[PDB]
Image 1 (cartoon, helix red, strand yellow):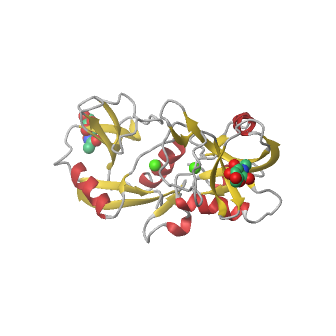
Image 2 (cartoon, chains in turn orange, yellow):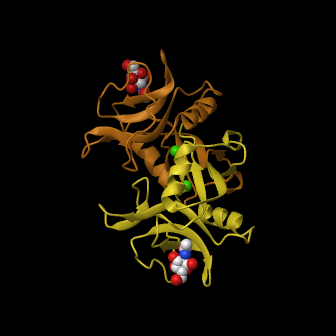
Image 3 (cartoon, chains in turn red, blue):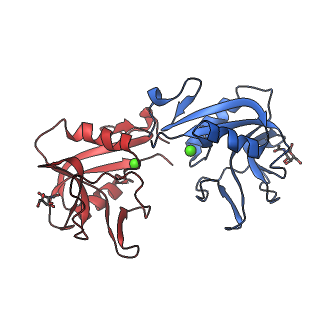
Length: 138
Length: 138
Ligand SMILES: CC(=O)N[C@@H]1[C@@H](O)[C@@H](O)[C@@H](CO)O[C@H]1O
Ligand SMILES: CC(=O)N[C@@H]1[C@@H](O)[C@@H](O)[C@@H](CO)O[C@H]1O
Ligand SMILES: [Ca+2]
Ligand SMILES: [Ca+2]
């Protein structure tokens, strides 16, 4: 429900959402907490246009090769899904993914995974940047 | 997931969605079918900014005093909710609404209901304009 003018300074507008591409260095759980500290949440990716919007941003730098996003293995439902509890619609796994290690998802840029989703086994101690999202739904 | 440039000609952009404010004259069921004919669906209103975007458009004319939207009494769940099966989040009923007549929802402009939701008892034979939505989720 966001418009351009709704995005906080340093956030980017796409597709009714505002996004923060945060260059800090945290674990997945740390990253979830960080986005919450901004009245926001790790990004959820509902469609291929949003997937490609994200890829366009991550592809414009080369320093970092993964960014945490808002999905992880879900014990209750026994699947990977968004942290808001909603199942995947768009499917964005890279070649050969998921490994099914009951881990946490990132966009990964490694070998044949070209800014596509990977499940990483370590939700705690693997430090990287992250992507937060708001949709101004109020 | 829509951007401005994604909206078909005659549709309007707001908040990641494209909207058709169609001035044809159909019943609610007719209106649901019409939006489907456009690879689209009667509008669902997830937030107060989208509610007010819609109000801004409907308020700019005076000929019509109601427009069909994508919600109706749901037999299974025994409530009013969106036709996509999802429950209300934003609550947009006008003063004194719902009547609880197990009907179909419109934006209504009548007496103290000032372009806010009403439940109309007749889902079939009450002819009016409607609001279709796409979110380009592909
Ligand atoms: C943080 C991240 O995604 N790391 C991935 C890892 O999970 C593994 O999939 C590997 C190939 O064995 O590529 C990595 O560098
Ligand atoms: C189409 C529509 O919403 N019509 C509403 C009707 O449902 C009723 O609520 C009435 C007041 O009794 O206002 C009407 O004209
Ligand atoms: Ca999203
Ligand atoms: Ca909507």
